[PDB]
Length: 158
Image (cartoon, rainbow, N blue to C red; front, side, top):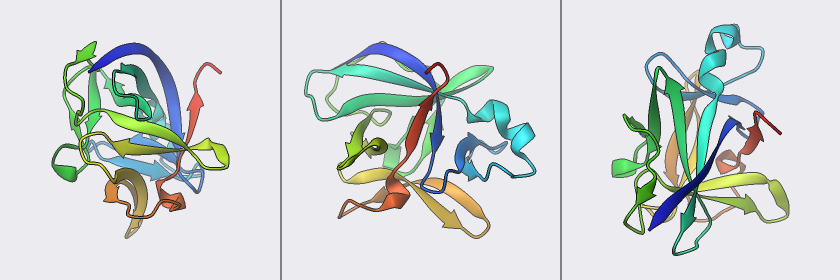
């Protein structure tokens, strides 16, 4: 079971220092910081990362949420990325949750972070180039070390 401990406003960057944002179609994408749309994208680059106490410690249990009038929360339900129309909850009774990810440092690189789905073991948040877009996806990572599934997390107050 999980209990919410604290929340922080955060900026998430991929392996190429592109910044995670939510586009108008509610899709999580990565922008170059010289992107001509970076002015309009700015409010949608701020994420609420909530950290949870976990009765079965497996990594740092977090939810990733966005505020746009209402708060929505990243979900790995059905092994795809989506947003649930929910605030991060105070408590979660089960040991796995489609909105809980395990955040862990990369070996030898304490600043680089990976996010594993707590509901689908072996599935990680990753950045993937798809045509001209860079998308946040959920990907089954057999072997770790893929830098495309490594991020840095910057606190808005830090």
